[PDB]
């Protein structure tokens, strides 16, 4: 049942795709490919040297596993996976095909409507609810891995894999609430058009992050663990928690309330993805009957730290066995 493939040299690499797909422009490297089968615009990704290190081989089995498992309206889904290789010992290339959306949330920023922010933030949180229910953290949610079409249907890309310190959670710079800090950072920018914390250095970010949320209180200074984390907080000036209204001028009161609860340093007391959906701000979008959870993902392969050759064969079988969904 193997069809026929074709070569093309792009950006110093050889894209070897079947006849089924045509035209490949960069949008490792992801091409904007036009389908001739369903006549849609599919996303075609060719990975960065998939098995040329032990981690690359693991980041490949995980990515393909994560994708052949997630099934949610706001989470990228796998349509196809292929290899130009005819056998197992010739398998060194992996291709992943999804749906291609318009652009990203970084591209839709601009002064945004509170109802347009309502609909995107709701989609992000509903997408995280189905991701978190399968025990997975994005850890680097930025508007660039939040793809949107023309109708504002949103899909989360690049979950569970990984100027740059802009959206990182304080406790990580552990807990699913790491992505809730990123959600608040995107929402703040959508409501205005200004990066809440656009810091350059690792330390400066923490000084900018604590400039709005305040300095960690007596309760948290006891909760805190790390010596350098303790000896940096006590080395930086005393800062009180700022009023969100004073910075979030004109914004919907229920939008100012969510962000205040979202952007707290306390991980044990940070609003969850499931909890944030039933919040007053999303009263129009919320519906408990159409908010799906995830069918258990076999994360047993993580505790294993085997050899390249073993990862490759596991990745090999998930490609052969793959059944294309309607
Ligand atoms: C093809 C592909 C493979 C894997 C994953 C992905 O998450 N695996 C993680 C393990 C979860 C995601 C994708 N898909 C995209 N991966 C990167 N970039 N990318 C841009 C788009 C656009 O639709 C788009 C189009 C024009 C401009 C901007 C954006 C799309 C859909 C993707």
Image (tube, rainbow, N blue to C red):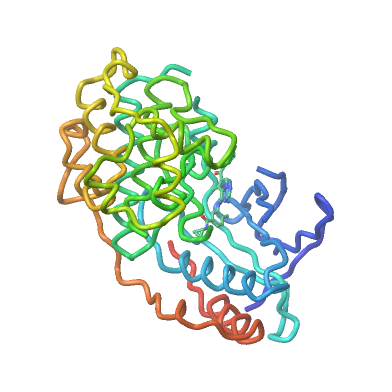
The x and y percentages for residue 119 are 31, 33
The x and y percentages for residue 79 are 51, 61
Residue at 64% across / 69% down in the picture?
56
Question: Is residue 190 at all visible to an observer of this figure?
Answer: yes
Q: Nearer the viewer, residue 323 or 93?
A: 93
94 to 211, vertically: above or below = below
* Quarter of the C terminus within the rendering: bottom left
Residue at 36% across / 28% down in the picture?
212
Image label count:
0
Residue at 46% across / 38% down in the picture?
206
The x and y percentages for residue 116 are 35, 26
- In-image side of 22 versus 81 (left or right): right
267 to 88, vertically: above or below = above
- In-image side of 5 versus 257 (left or right): right
* Quarter of the N terminus within the rendering: bottom right
The x and y percentages for residue 191 are 37, 22
Residue at 24% across / 43% down in the picture?
218
Q: Nearer the viewer, residue 305 or 127?
A: 305
26 to 254, vertically: above or below = below
Question: Is residue 131 at all visible to an observer of this figure?
Answer: no
């Amino acid at each position: 049942e193997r069809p026929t493939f074709y070569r093309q040299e792009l950006n110093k690499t050889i894209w070897e795709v079947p006849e089924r797909y045509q035209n490949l422009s960069p949008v490792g490297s992801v091409c904007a490919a036009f389908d001739t089968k369903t006549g849609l615009r599919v996303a075609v990704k060719k990975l960065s040297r998939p098995f040329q290190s032990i981690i690359h081989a693991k980041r490949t089995y995980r990515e393909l596993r994560l994708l052949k498992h997630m099934k949610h309206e706001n989470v990228i889904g796998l349509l196809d996976v292929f290899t130009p290789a005819r056998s197992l010992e010739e398998f060194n290339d992996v291709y992943l095909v999804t749906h291609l959306m318009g652009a990203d949330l970084n591209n839709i920023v601009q002064k945004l409507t509170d109802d347009h922010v309502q609909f995107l933030i709701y989609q992000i949180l509903r997408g995280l609810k189905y991701i978190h229910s399968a025990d997975i953290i994005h850890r680097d949610l930025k508007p660039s891995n939040l793809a949107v079409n023309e109708d504002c249907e949103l899909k989360i890309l690049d979950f569970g894999l990984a100027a740059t310190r802009w959206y990182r959670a304080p406790e990580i710079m552990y807990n699913q609430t790491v992505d809730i800090w990123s959600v608040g950072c995107i929402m703040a920018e959508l409501l205005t058009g200004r990066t809440l914390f656009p810091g350059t250095d690792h330390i400066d970010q923490l000084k900018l992050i604590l400039r709005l949320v305040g300095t960690p209180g007596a309760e948290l200074l006891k909760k805190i663990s790390s010596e350098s984390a303790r000896n940096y907080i006590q080395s930086l000036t005393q800062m009180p928690k700022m009023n969100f209204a004073n910075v979030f001028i004109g914004a919907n009161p229920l939008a100012v309330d969510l962000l205040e609860k979202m952007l707290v340093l306390d991980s044990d007391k940070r609003i969850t993805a499931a909890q944030a959906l039933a919040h007053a701000y999303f009263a129009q979008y919320h519906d408990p009957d159409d908010e799906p959870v995830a069918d258990p993902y076999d994360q047993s392969f993580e505790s294993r730290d085997l050899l390249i050759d073993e990862w490759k064969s596991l990745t090999y079988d998930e490609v052969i066995s793959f059944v294309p969904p309607p």
